[PDB]
Length: 9
Length: 9
Length: 12
Length: 12
Image: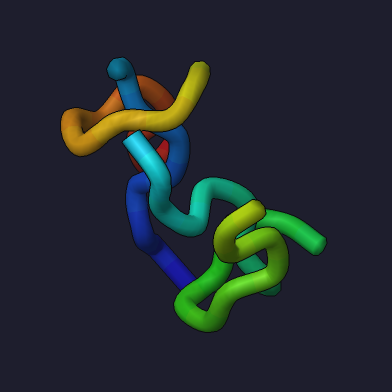
């Protein structure tokens, strides 16, 4: 498990 | 904006 | 439950 | 820390 998660709108 | 953001693992 | 490779909170 | 399509919480 190594996914980058939350973002910027 | 509108994607999965919190995931399982 | 976290930040994984399968979803948890997908859409609304 | 929000929605979007560019990364804000990368792998840490």
